[PDB]
Length: 301
Length: 306
Ligand SMILES: O=C1C[C@@H](C(=O)NCC(=O)N(c2ccccc2)c2ccccc2)c2ccccc21
Ligand SMILES: O=C1C[C@@H](C(=O)NCC(=O)N(c2ccccc2)c2ccccc2)c2ccccc21
Image (cartoon, rainbow over all chains, first blue to last red; front, side, top):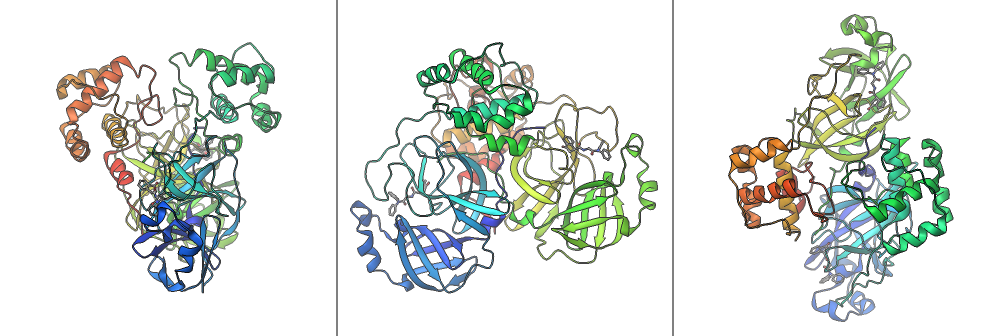
């Protein structure tokens, strides 16, 4: 019983964090096997960012210009290359603490744990969702660049986010570990902005189920709805559409509580229109959308 | 920018978790040097818990009646002893992943991270507070007993909590690592229940300071209050009394933001009496009390661990 914002244990990722220095800049990197991954903007000065030619900037760098340190030890850099917006530093030692891992690109709505680091050392761990507008709402300061986001499933780390920049609105932008940005962002100095955001409907439904597992019931009503009618209401209130896959993914929580998916949608429908009436669900006065149906199953069953 | 409920990195603690099995019961243990610490209720059958005589139960166990496993390697038990509500199993090898560590007893209102574990395998980590009523509002299922709570101080893990039971309201009770319970709970089947709880005032104020640091300023107003006047309103909404010590420890956040402590109390007074009128603070439509003053400073100043 209980329901908390729970992160993955971070130890397998802590064993991969390093510090990467190129000239006057230091940021974080991720050491897997004999490669260190970090944002390619490490190689840029402030003046370079106005109009960078990353391929030329990198031609003017050599292996010796990159200082890589794992705790107190310098790694020898023996090669360098760029894949999209990620720099890959080859080093002469494979990380002995390399976990089982994969790189995955996640969809909006999906959650992960962030290990916020500075200078290759950890500050803390917390859960984030990829927003529909491809930002995350993290907690990050200068020098957090190169911190990563991940999930852990049957002993295997799936890295899905590398942190690159904070946007003027105070939210965060980055890439997958193949170096492709999430959303319309770029690693140079230009006006760029996140669009309008929406609420992750399937996550809100998963959280309602969680509330029912923990004994909340007051929002269940006597009504039902169709998927198409629910989606008409959702759009008015800037909620993402709910798809049949979503319904299917919510099956297990449906099974466990007795509450048909469309009946829970009928509950949300009334909440979207009429609000929470001064009431709380699982410790909150707003509808929470950063728990997936898998986050809920993991903690509640 | 941003302000999250941030847990400690858990790697130093993950390397200490093991499984302990006695009869049909399996729960988690903490392996530090050549000792394994776990709840002593591991030695009890369901029959025994009505009125356990732990020293009579324990004297009847042999070393070989305990099965301790690190992963799927057996740690042979070579000695046992009880200290308060914790069992200490001496084992035949020292954990080579033992971090620097200390046992510390925390006070109510203080915060720590829980590493929730099942069958000796960590499943996740979250940050929570010790409630005024000495419970924790954790997230735990059957099997979680022996899971621990901790803080990190530079390179040192300060262990503060070991999980023993869920009470009937769905909150959590346990001990320090010397096996003394927080609060008036006991490790037997009783009708014990969670006493009346309050909101941790100082922590709410700390989080309003976090909000200001992050640019969320709408609840700042032109009024002030005295400490005594404030406490009258605190009493009515079931908030802990604010003391001059609490006022002192908000000193640094006050200095950083330029908002006097008693002006921030004036802002909270108004939020209590009026509510939020539809608005949010740091993404919440409720007043949050699980960040301490030091927690705000640590996150906002990018403190790391070694
Ligand atoms: O969460 C973060 C990470 C950090 C950040 O935003 N880094 C970005 C950054 O430093 N640059 C850059 C700038 C000048 C030379 C080279 C790179 C940048 C610029 C444009 C596009 C992409 C990268 C930060 C700073 C202050 C507060 C919060 C935070
Ligand atoms: O958060 C937890 C941990 C788990 C718990 O509360 N276990 C308690 C428990 O197993 N016993 C006991 C019982 C029979 C023999 C021996 C011990 C118990 C009884 C009284 C006093 C203290 C210990 C649990 C069960 C359900 C949901 C959530 C949770």
